[PDB]
Image 1: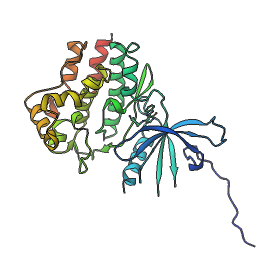
Image 2: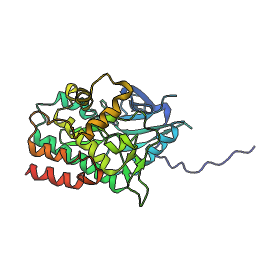
Image 3: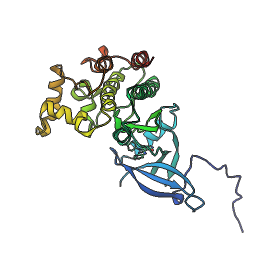
Length: 293
Ligand SMILES: N[C@H]1CC[C@@H](Nc2cc[nH]c(=O)c2-c2nc3ccccc3[nH]2)CC1
């Protein structure tokens, strides 16, 4: 009786079996799906490694697959490490688990531990990861303090790439078609007006991320809370056009409390109305380093 001979099974370390991936809790609820803390426990004794698992809620599978392929080929100390995948056409993205979470979770609870010097070092690391992303012709489109993971007191990593798009060679921007649900209070005017995304658009979002970092991610002084005070919080569908109008008028987020003018000036260089007039990530690194020593 016939039976197929089995060759030597080259066991894949980036392949995680669904049966061993055991859910612990929810970490976040992103744009398209969910992120959960799991323990890959093949020995079934609660000793397995803790991993961050990104999946979809039951179309948008194409976006997750493209996000997986982007992260798989990113290698930088300030970019969350890709660990692998869990296959079914359904797919799950496995990433390293950073128990400190994002700056949004970490900063309000560790104010006494993080001084201005440490805040400027995080800013340098965010810029380096962002510059590495830009050099590989990519636009992040979701740079906020909530997407900056804390590895330790001395190291941060860009931890989510759900909205990352590639900029075509011999082209300066990407045109978004699905601009819902956009983080409008973090976006540059060209993103809000014409739905165009340049590298300079990410520099604008960095300025906003830097403002959050300096305010230790306090909810009351958040970019959304502050801009809604400037434009009005009861405009509904007229919020974005009022936001564009306010930015055109020259109005920008105020100086964070206890932030020196020289840091605020670097932040202002990120907020030039025209993308071509904005500072680069490399000029920001230079700027922060100069203030460090
Ligand atoms: N705010 C979004 C950041 C991106 C995603 N989160 C990741 C991703 C990859 N690796 C991680 O370790 C985490 C992580 N989030 C945590 C939330 C609380 C505590 C620990 C956490 N770890 C979703 C939430």
